[PDB]
Amino acid sequence: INPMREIKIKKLSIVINVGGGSSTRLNNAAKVLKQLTSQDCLFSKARYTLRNFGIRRNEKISVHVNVSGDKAMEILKKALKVREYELSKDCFNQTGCFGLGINEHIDLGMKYDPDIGIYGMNFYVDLKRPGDRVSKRKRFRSKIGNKQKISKEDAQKWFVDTFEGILL
Amino acid sequence: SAGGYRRKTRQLLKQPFRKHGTPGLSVYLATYRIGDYVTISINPSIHKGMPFKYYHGRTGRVFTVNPKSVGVVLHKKVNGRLSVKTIFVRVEHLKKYKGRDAFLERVNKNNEILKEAREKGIKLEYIRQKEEGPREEFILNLDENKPVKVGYEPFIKVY
Amino acid sequence: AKSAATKRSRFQVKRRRRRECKTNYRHRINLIKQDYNKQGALKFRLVVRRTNTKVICQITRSYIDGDRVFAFADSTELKNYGVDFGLKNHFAFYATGFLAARRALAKLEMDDLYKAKETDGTYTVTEDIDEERRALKVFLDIGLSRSTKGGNTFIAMKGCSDAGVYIPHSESKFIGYEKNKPFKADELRDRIFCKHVSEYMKTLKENDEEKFKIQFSDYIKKNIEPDNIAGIYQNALDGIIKNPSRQEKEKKDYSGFKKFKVEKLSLEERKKRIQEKLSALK
RNA sequence: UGUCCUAAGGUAGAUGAAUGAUGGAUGGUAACCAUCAGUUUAUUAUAAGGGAAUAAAUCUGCUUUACUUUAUGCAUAUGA
RNA sequence: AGGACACUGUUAUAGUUAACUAUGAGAAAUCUUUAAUUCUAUGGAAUUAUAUAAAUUAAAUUUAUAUAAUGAAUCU
RNA sequence: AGUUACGGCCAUAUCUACUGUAAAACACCGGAACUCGUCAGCUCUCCGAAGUUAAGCCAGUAAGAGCCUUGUGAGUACUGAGAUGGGAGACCGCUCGGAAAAGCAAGGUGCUGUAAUU
Ligand SMILES: [Mg+2]
Ligand SMILES: [Mg+2]
């Protein structure tokens, strides 16, 4: 097999959905993502005003951080142990990605620190083969070939081999 | 449809089908000199230098060349007479008027015939445009041509 | 609720050179405009492009049927002067345009009146002589690449000004310039010569002997020492001022290469292949 | 239609808009995050018409060309 | 004008696994299209040699101006 | 005889499926000591040459969609000039001239300018 046909991990994304008017719940949760990885947080705003969710327009809601490198492997190997390395069949998309969510970040292995509080988050991963610079460059922009795109069953193969786990 | 500068332009200032967008480089590379012949065609994608809508498609002559404008002289039909107009337009609204090219070639070739006949004692046999008169004679052959009988035919309804 | 056929018929296809993501058509037209009075005077432009392992520099003047080149220079021509280890460095952009502008004047015989300067790094723009012809005028095409402070494209126009060809530019995009201060001419002189490359090479030896053999392997395989690079680079510039002429190649004939060519299938084989496809079904 | 704008004026640079499909703890028709598709459906102060997809649209920076003086044309004329 | 249902506005019913396939009706403020007619311009000046500039170009290099000579070219 | 850098005309050059290329070139590709840029060397910027022809670029196949062109449609629809022609009217017929589209068949699927390398 040619080594350009391999599958890898492009990036991982973390999202903490808090909804509130207090900046103290934001700034407490902003320290948790810095405590997990040394990157800094990035905020998000609202699109409209929804009374049923306690949301007004142009107002801060949540935080998210995009990570890459080998640091993403240490966060991913922790999160799979919470579900005992067991996943469903429908978590895989048409394009190849998948995700999961954990109710408690204390199960990740941090300290309590009670004034910070207890939160929860959900993760999402990306898979790309080598040769993905073609659709991303400015000069010489073009499409990807039809032979190199990942499908749903290709995620079902690579997940079991790199992590010995159970499919449901 | 009141009296304004751009009245009643719905199909005259519309860009045609599958041809939208800013013009190309072959427009900008052309040059103009004093005494040429130029037709006017509005490109409705630039808004600096458009003439009035009356002059769309009339040919004139170029008398001045400015850093941003070209001067064209024309003729308008005011109530009794034929007057003289001057307008300044941009380069992206013009076109080189053809129609003298067959004439200017005839000038250059007749000037060569005059030169070769100077060395001889003959009279000039110039080139002028042809004339069409009565129908000339021709010769048909009945060896391979057979006549076809034509007649009427009875009427038949379409259903 | 439109069909699949109407969505294709209403499609307007962009231009061919825009389709391949190679040019910016609004940027080109503003470069080659001209006032209408100067009919006989065509503009010049210098093109600086790089491939993955080369630097290409051309001087052109545009026409209706297509462009034409006046003089070109290739970064792979520097083997004749002794620089063949770095073909994409900060020095490689400088010497290529320096050979380009030196080659253009020798077509016009202005080599005696306008000669090269010494590579000091001071911000200067050449001027006119009192009685003779004025200097030549060339503008710069940046292409599609973004503009930064220490870019490699901006140092190639520095090489054209040192050959004597007049190019309007300002010192704001150079290395060692800060606002409201005199220009640090010696700091620019350390990036023109490959001093930062040599001190990275000296640092890697005592720090990581394993990583250094991977990164600078052609510097290892050729017998090239880091403490002497600018002695070789300075010797390379002196040969260009002596002789800028090209060297001719003999013309061979390549007609045996025609065998890697596929024609289109004819009409007789097209109608034959259809009935064999219909034969297997019945 | 008798209005609005120190930016909604000037210029440089960066940029797949509206929407749809499939997924992700609490999360539902509808909160946020990733992936793929996306020929102009979106926006451009306003009536209608015309124009614009490396964009005249959305962001980031810097500024006051919302100047002073010689001559001429176009609506448009016999004529302010 | 004629034409078309492909864009914008409109309308009757049957089928196949919201999408495709049929037979019907249409447009003063709709257009992938498009005649008969109406109108604008050319059908004689161009080339050569020499000179002038304070314009213009990298440049006798262009853009312009003079003087000399060489001419009747579509039907009524 | 093909590539590669600038292009002119801007679909015969687009879109959806499969298949192939010796040399050289073009790419993918390895990293952040310095200039520069981000939440993230993803993009941009700056140094490189272990690996790979899987993709991109180039060239092919399809009773393929789309575009381009010839014939039929058809002297059919329509129309410039005219008469003490016909009809309650709506309108129709004749003489001397000009002359269509949509479909339905058959065929095609970029051409080219300056320079460089095998
Ligand atoms: Mg204005
Ligand atoms: Mg505006």
Image (cartoon, coloured by chain):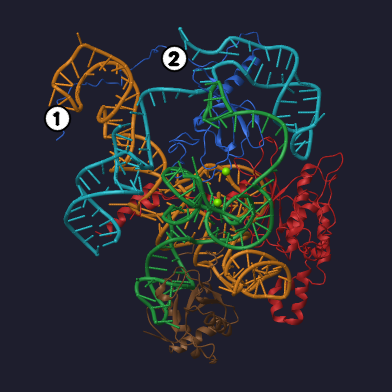
Chain colours: A brown, B blue, C red, D green, E cyan, F orange
Label 2: state its secondary structure: loop
Residue D6 lies, in percent from the top left, at 61, 56
Residue E54, above or below F102? above
Q: Amino acid at mark 2?
A: Glu
Along the line of sight, the residue nearer the viewer: C32 or C219? C32
| Residue B42 horizontal side relative to residue F32, left or right | left
User: Is label 1 on the same chain as label 2?
Assistant: yes
Which of the chains bears the disc numbered 2? B
Q: Which residue is mark 1?
A: B156
**Residue C246 visible, this angle:** no
Name the N-terminal-most of marks 1 and 2: 2
Pointers 1 and 2 in contact (C-beta within 8 Å)? no
Label 1: state its secondary structure: loop
Along the line of sight, the residue nearer the viewer: A102 or A60? A60
Residue at 61% x, 46% y is C29
Crowd class of label 1 (few under 14; some 14 to 19; many from 20; radius 10 Å): few
Question: As drawn, which residue projects farthest toward the right?
Answer: C130
Residue at 69% x, 40% y is C42
Quadrant of image for the C terminus of chain A: bottom left
Residue C92, above or below F42? above
Q: Amino acid at mark 1?
A: Ile
Q: Quadrant of residue C209?
A: bottom right
Which of the chains bears the disc numbered 1? B
| Residue C142 horizontal side relative to residue F11, left or right | right
| Residue C32 horizontal side relative to residue A7, left or right | right
- Which mark, residue B132? 2
Q: Give the number of callouts.
A: 2
Q: Say if disc 2 is inside 8 Å of ligand 1.
A: no
Crowd class of label 2 (few under 14; some 14 to 19; many from 20; radius 10 Å): few
**Residue A130 visible, this angle:** yes
